Image (cartoon, rainbow over all chains, first blue to last red; front, top):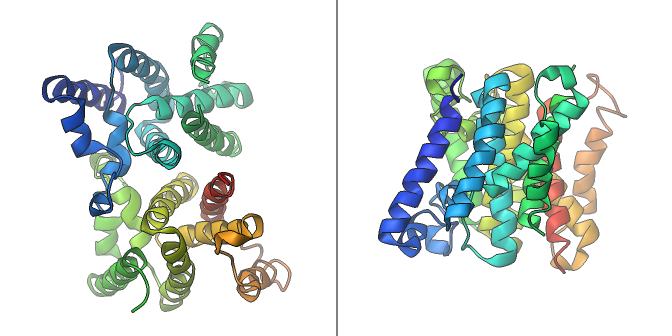
Length: 173
Length: 182
């Protein structure tokens, strides 16, 4: 079993983004991918999303990609790539907007999306067991500890998203 | 022209597309602007949004652009273009997903985003009256005489449509969040 394209291309890219940042420096890269930090840049749409692709530390990228590898691979595997992409896009945007709103356009990371995967995977397994998707009991808290690991709101919004779609999804059948 | 840049470009973009669809026919333009309909296109990212650019009838694009211009406008003036772009992006995404999910990839319209702006606008005025934004009581009602003139003043069945609740949810979300700061 190998992880799907979505899950893979995200990991690799975030590794390639960390790439540039280490070399060129955090500053230079965010100058390129950061959430619109000036009106002049407001129409540069990629910015609404590319901020997820940026990490500032070893631990930061390491845990985010582990949660993304495990959750993100399970979702793409059982429910498909489309399901992963949307959860990602919406959660990246929502969280990005809540972050930008309260603390400035200078941030980066795949933690907003991770929290969405945590709320989506966990919720479905609980509501729609047979669906195949669920958050392993042991890992519930390597992650609820990643949920309580931070105490954030730019993380709640993302959780809300995961939770939202998961509700919709365990709402069909 | 008083309407801001976002509001303005979106309307022009919709007219330019509707025209093209007319032309090349709805089929062709969807081919290009429809939510990914085949794995081969899954990574053509514009598609996840561009679906909102297409309309299938005169009355479709009309009321859509009317509410967009009335509502979109207001937001963009009183709250900035950023606020309108993000509302447009998150609601286009969440509502197109729901749609696709339950009814496939062939759709279109700016109705999902209209449900979001209405919800936001309305909700923000009710919670943050002073923010300056609100949905004119009559207007609110030209939505409610309507949820209540298809639901109550009935016609079809119940227009509380699949993709329109997610769109609404988004706006109600961001509104609830913006009326939460102060």
